[PDB]
Amino acid sequence: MLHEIPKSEILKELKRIGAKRVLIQSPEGLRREAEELAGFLEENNIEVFLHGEINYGACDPADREAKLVGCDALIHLGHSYMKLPLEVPTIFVPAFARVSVVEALKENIGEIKKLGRKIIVTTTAQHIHQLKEAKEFLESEGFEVSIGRGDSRISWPGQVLGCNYSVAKVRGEGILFIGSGIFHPLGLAVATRKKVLAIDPYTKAFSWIDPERFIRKRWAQIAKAMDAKKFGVIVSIKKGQLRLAEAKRIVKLLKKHGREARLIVMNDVNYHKLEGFPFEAYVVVACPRVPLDWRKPVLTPKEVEILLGLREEYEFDEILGGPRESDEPFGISIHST
Amino acid sequence: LHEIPKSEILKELKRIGAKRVLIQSPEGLRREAEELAGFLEENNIEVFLHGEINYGACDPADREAKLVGCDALIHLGHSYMKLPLEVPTIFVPAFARVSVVEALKENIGEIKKLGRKIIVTTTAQHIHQLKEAKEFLESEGFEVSIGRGDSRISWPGQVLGCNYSVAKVRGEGILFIGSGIFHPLGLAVATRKKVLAIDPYTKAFSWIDPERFIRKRWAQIAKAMDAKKFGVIVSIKKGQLRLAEAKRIVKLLKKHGREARLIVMNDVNYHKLEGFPFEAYVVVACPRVPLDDYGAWRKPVLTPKEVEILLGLREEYEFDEILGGPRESDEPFGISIHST
Ligand code: SF4
Ligand code: SF4
């Protein structure tokens, strides 16, 4: 259960810029809400088209598609803005979970103390609105809380993305991750080399991350690719995912070391679409969730470096941004150009 | 003609000074795409392969090519259909080698039942064989009629799953040369004429009966009768975007008591839509999607024409075709290069 979408504030914003037709994109868990919002803005004299693709991040705005079908603006549900040039005015509408993080923290104080006195705290967008309460609670328990601002791919200090842990690159004896799943906590452990404790707000369960098994299974994938002679280097056209210079460099690099290499252009990166190609191994240079989370070895740019022996220590693939001036609001936002 | 003219392609590329090209390919030519790329790269042209699986010239990857800085696009497996293109595009049609005459001779007794004046049609892969099929049928006493088709078609006599314009000519019965049932079925429902399909490989013939198919559609329409919320889908694929027609359908459903929302997609498939509240869908893009579903759609999915029947505006069934305008010329039987 999440907090309700700010229909009124949204409508007001569209009217402010004067918008007659808008495209609404939404993530898996907000399909029913996207239609409610559409039926609402329509009764208010605004033509609405729903984006039928399932959105997975602000790194993939449907501004191009909006343009193509004549929409004045774009409404992006469920995610906050990340620095990207946009072709049509876009209103981001973050989703905030109501579950209490503090309750999950109080249940696990003992485990958190094992982390250290000065600790780095991180969380995902859905709990970012409760980060301040979590910080004050931890401080009242004797911790010094270090929260990093992060870079331009990030919306709020302390927020991590599966492909970006810049807010965690600060000083601390250990890292506390507030949220569910193991992908974020795992990336944090690999990216920072510090001990990580993950606490799931819903179940209140805790997990001490051990990257070992993960790194092992990845090396096994690297080993298999060591025998390959033919590689496919994949990029995605999604605005916040396109890493062409980096892909072109991996191609040049595989060739230098006696491998055949081909740059492959896609939108959604699905191994399923590549089964008929002759490549023996693949390198995905886009969202790292793809290779890190395939009948043939699929790797990240970092792993291909390791495979070619040009890198020794295992590293998590990240999409970094440059410095960020301000922070996004804890509510909707409008962005243009 | 039955091979990728690597050298003819390099020539046309060197001629326009292309340095970086994107190559798209259908499922059956994935390995050919990479061999062509290897060949072009040995000749000073950077090559990128489009990773998506292509299903027709109705889905050119010129925009994507533009997005990654390619100065040209190579479209393998299909011939050109009229559409604006953002970069010079070379179309490399696939031509099957099989000679079709033997299979016609074998079934000459069945072809006779179509009548004296017959309409002859085939798909892209056997198009170069139409001249021979014509000479044979004429040498057997038939009067062969071959329609030019519209701008969505590349050569006279060619049908597409969504376009049977070449068959809208004077003629008693229709002969279809090819394998598979989708095309012959589309012909029968689109022209409401008698269709005889002959497979050039097996020499097997088939008199087409749309009855089964039509009943199945009525059924589907029935299942949507008690639906109130409708999703009306369009695809942003260049040769498939039918925005005006989709909007019209949204307006029509609303005027008739139903709720309807226009949905924009690229690849149209049910899974992406499962989370939406809509009870029924209307696909206003490629007709093969709703008319040839193997079972991926868990909710009733219809074509624009079927909606009109459901709403009670149309009485007889009609095939959802994507029509083009007059075509001034015909594409070559080999590669072609276009730039709009
Ligand atoms: S690149 Fe991948 S991890 Fe990063 S925001 Fe997009 S979908 Fe999420
Ligand atoms: S039948 Fe569908 S995929 Fe084939 S050419 Fe027509 S629109 Fe394109």
Image (cartoon, coloured by chain):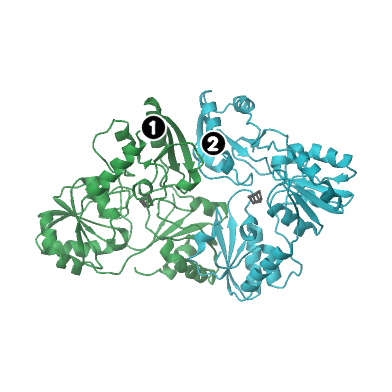
Chain colours: A cyan, B green
Residue type highlighted by circle 2: Arg
Residue B126 placement: quadrant: bottom left
Where is residue B162 shown, x and y percent of the image? 33, 48
At x 65%, y 57%, the residue is A288
- Which chain is disc 1 placed on? B
Residue B248 has which mark? 1
Residue A32 has which mark? 2
Please identify, in this view, whether the residue under mark 2 or under mark 1 is nearer the observer.
Answer: 2
Q: Are marks 2 and 1 on the same chain?
A: no
Q: Is residue B50 visible?
A: no
At x 61%, y 48%, the residue is A239
Relative to residue B95, is residue B33 drawn left or right? Answer: right
Relative to residue B335, is residue A69 drawn left or right? Answer: right
- Which chain is disc 2 placed on? A
Between residue A209 and residue B129, name the one nearer to us: A209
Q: Residues within 10 Å of mark 1 (few under 14, many from 20)?
A: few
State if disc 1 and disc 2 touch (CB < 8 Å). Answer: no
Q: Relative to residue B323, is residue A310 depicted above or below?
A: below
Relative to residue B88, is residue B190 drawn left or right? Answer: left
Q: Residues within 10 Å of mark 2 (few under 14, many from 20)?
A: some
Where is residue A255 shown, x and y percent of the image? 62, 72
Q: Relative to residue A33, is residue B126 depicted above or below?
A: below
Q: Element at badge 2?
A: helix
At x 34%, y 44%, the residue is B322
Where is residue A234 shown, x and y percent of the image? 58, 60
Q: Is residue B167 visible?
A: yes
